Amino acid sequence: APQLIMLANVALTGE
Amino acid sequence: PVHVEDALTYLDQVKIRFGSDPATYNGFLEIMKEFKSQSIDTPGVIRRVSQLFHEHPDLIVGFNAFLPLGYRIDIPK
Image (cartoon, rainbow over all chains, first blue to last red; front, side, top):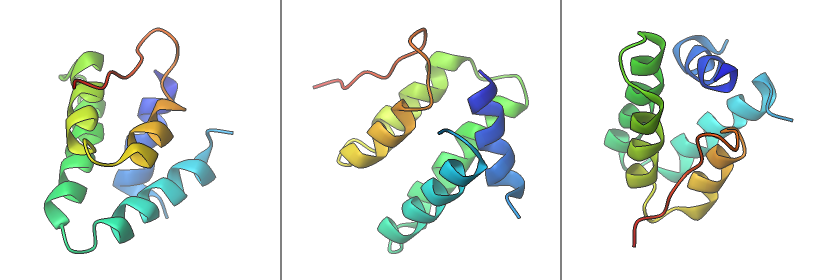
């Protein structure tokens, strides 16, 4: 799930 | 288009809607963060969300638009 990895990434570092 | 923009707004939408409930926000991050660790399975991610946003369709729906046909989301009555 590439969308799950990108989701957590933005949550852990989305800026 | 499930991109950095879609994920960004989602987080901001979950923060405002739950401005009086930080517990819910911290819970969502735990699911995603826990997934990155490669410990929690897929079913576990959709399960938490399905329970976290039990009274929020626009939330469970917004996330549903990211999950593929394989791992869909259920709405336990």
